[PDB]
Length: 140
Length: 195
Length: 201
Image 1: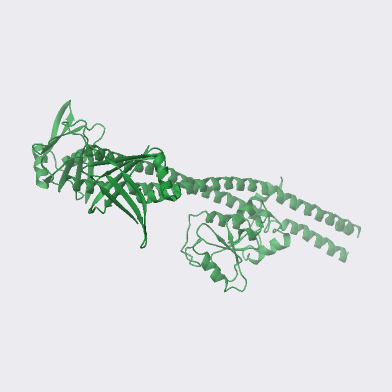
Image 2 (image 1 turned 90 degrees about the vertical axis):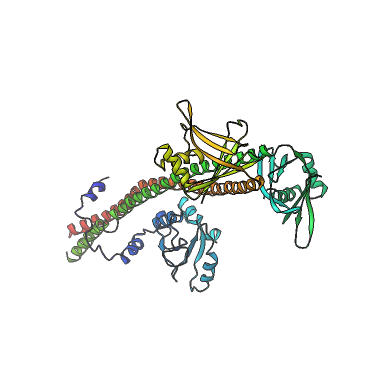
């Protein structure tokens, strides 16, 4: 109970080494096991989202879909959401529009490390049960 | 008590349009009142359950695609022909270089063209009005759906932001408290080694 | 190009619905062609802009205001307080139409008509048009329903999830603080160990 107002009484709690932070968060997660919690069960997953009418065209956005909420959930559950399907991608999530699934499969053949293609319910089932449901039933 | 109207022609007079009126009770399968008109004379027929079902017994095949081909023909390749004096109407499903009969009615004309016309369009302009009213309604409904949708998004994000603040408040350098106990460990241990 | 058809009843024929069709180019003032029918026969007439000028000025009203009135009368723009009435003699092919206030009729205009030699042809045309019109609204309503469905789904989904998220946000902090205090007391164990050792030496 005591740390409640004690934190707020801290003199400018942005104290030391507060700027270069990219490597100094994962270490915090790695060192102190931030990663052993349901809100980070997507910490080590790459997700590319099919919210673009054209793959890797950042302004072919299909905003207003329920995929936008999935982006929130993934990030909030530790997924690192990427806007470009580069060689570092491990998952791609498909919504209702399957118009680009053939392109993803053809583009998948070029990759040294191959990403998985999943339906939406994988994360929702993963989130709603607070535990990672496995992708193989969500493939394609 | 349902009804449909469709523009048609007849090969007997290929150059002019015709209008087929069907009116049925709760199902086309339950029989119906058919009505044909060029716009000047009244022509009508009544074929009910027993004989409409006997239709797809006469050509031996399923009532399913039989009534489907009827509603593709009657309810908007099919060819329609009618003779006024014999009042015999028939239509046939035409395929690529083959043709097989689909249906035929021996109608009976009625006295009164004006009224059938009049009611027909009565119905029609009624129907549009119905349509637009429903459209207005559903429009209002789903726009409401949308702005709740968006406002929920907004409160989602404010909740998320509160979440993020709480996260930072305790970890990233708030655990410097643990680091302080760590420094006390180091100071005590080194003073132990030196004393 | 605007068309407008209107179901009417002549006083001469209470039981017969007559149908007033209007065609004009965005503007009833510029002139129009008119067609009346009763399902067995049809009639057609014509009126020009200058005819409307003369009518509106023998009124002694501003043209345009009388045009709005005409929009109310012939294009069914009449309101609940509006009671127009229509009179036509098929023998004389003379139409006129009036306005009912003060318990009295008040005639608006009057047209020279002529019986058409091909009633059935104008009839086919009108009703083909009408069929098209209805069908359009039908399709539109269908689509509208579909998206109504989609939105009603989405709303429930997001509401439930936002509630669950608020729940977890309230749940988090005690998890965190138990997680901390455990290790912290252990470090206090180490602290007391080393501190007693230092005080002893």
